[PDB]
Amino acid sequence: MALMTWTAAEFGTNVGFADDQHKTIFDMVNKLHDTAATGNRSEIGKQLDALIDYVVMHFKSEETEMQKKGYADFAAHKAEHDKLVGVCADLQKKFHAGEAEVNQDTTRFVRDWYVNHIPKVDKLYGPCLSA
Ligand SMILES: [Fe+2]
Ligand SMILES: [Fe+2]
């Protein structure tokens, strides 16, 4: 089974770009999750790096919109993003040094992060960003 399934009831923000970017993240995580059950380390690394670049771009997209519109909780929301980016960059540094592996606990971690963040953090920006 795919690790991540997006539905509007669970995850819809009422902000079209953000929903689309979330769908992409779920698809990219699902590919990583599959590859993480193998020993194909170069393929894991390609998909890890692609995912993380995209995630940083998604967070930038949300942050630019939040900030330009004066969204109430922008700085606290960005703090959540920045802590995940730090975790991901650390994981890349270790993985690309040969010091850590990417496995399905890695991908379940990121799944956990998104399935909590989108409903509890991203949905809150819907009224502001959709207005
Ligand atoms: Fe998001
Ligand atoms: Fe967010």
Image (tube, rainbow, N blue to C red):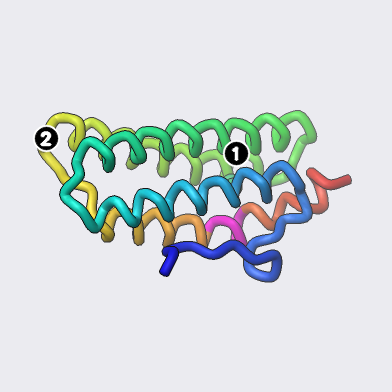
- Which residues fall within the magenta stretch? 117-121
Give the numbered dot on residue 75.
Answer: 1
Image height of 115 relative to 69, above or below = below
Residue sitting at x 78%, y 55%: 14
Residue type pointed to by label 1: Ala
Q: Residues within 10 Å of mark 1 (few under 14, many from 20)?
A: few
Q: Secondary structure at mark 2?
A: loop
Give the numbered dot on residue 98.
Answer: 2
Q: Quadrant of residue 30?
A: bottom left
Q: Point out residue 114 in the picture as x, y percentages from the top left corner.
A: 50, 56
The verdict on label 1 being within 8 Å of ligand 2 is no
* Mark positioned earlier in the residue sequence (2 or 1): 1
Residue 44 as seen in the image, left or right of residue 75: left
- Which residue occupies the foreground of this view, 21 or 46? 46
Q: Point out residue 63 in the picture as x, y percentages from the top left corner.
A: 63, 34
Residue type pointed to by label 2: Gly
Q: Residues within 10 Å of mark 2 (few under 14, many from 20)?
A: few
